[PDB]
Image 1: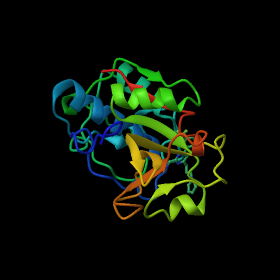
Image 2 (image 1 turned 90 degrees about the vertical axis):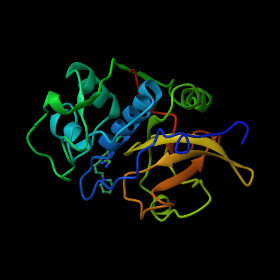
Image 3 (image 1 turned 60 degrees about the vertical axis):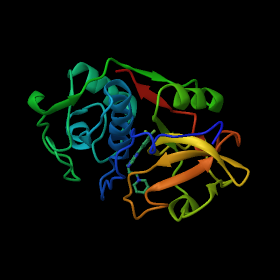
Length: 215
Ligand SMILES: *C(#N)C1=NC([C][C][C]N2[C][C][C][C][C]2)=[C]C(C2=[C]C(C(F)(F)F)=[C][C]=[C]2)=N1
């Protein structure tokens, strides 16, 4: 469709994951944006290791939460991130066991979308690929999402408490959206995904903490 993109159809997006009981959403957001850039740069991707991030990004709080920017900084400084197959997800924080022989991607830094600018976010998604985004995911209504374009007037754009991955944008039945990849399993939402309101005054803080890795 004109003025839309869906990166899942272009091979930039791996299967939806389940973080389990661990607060590693940021590690799944981060590996997601890295996966997209792997495909962009090399023509192929593989699953990258969230557990590598949870365990080794000491600036974040493991299963207590974190920021995607810190993970990108880590992959750059560490000269790599392992594959999921080299360093599998266990759902709790463990000692850092990074080994460069399982290295599957690299990072030369990151950029942040100007705060609150959805138009800038759309150009990022159009010109880069999948972009890491933070949202207010606290509402009951967010959690019980199944179909349509999500909008709730109660969403607080200043309460950013959950990390997700913007993998496209479009319009459905006259409602502009972002295609959002979550890490609560394929059972959640619509096969792991949520369509969130686009251009509805930065609904849920969608454009407030957006970043992508340079590769
Ligand atoms: C993700 N996952 C995640 N987890 C946490 C800790 C657990 C939060 N809590 C939410 C309600 C129900 C059960 C558990 C914290 C964060 C977090 C993420 C961000 C970011 F901006 F990066 F999106 C900011 C603050 C906290 N994410």
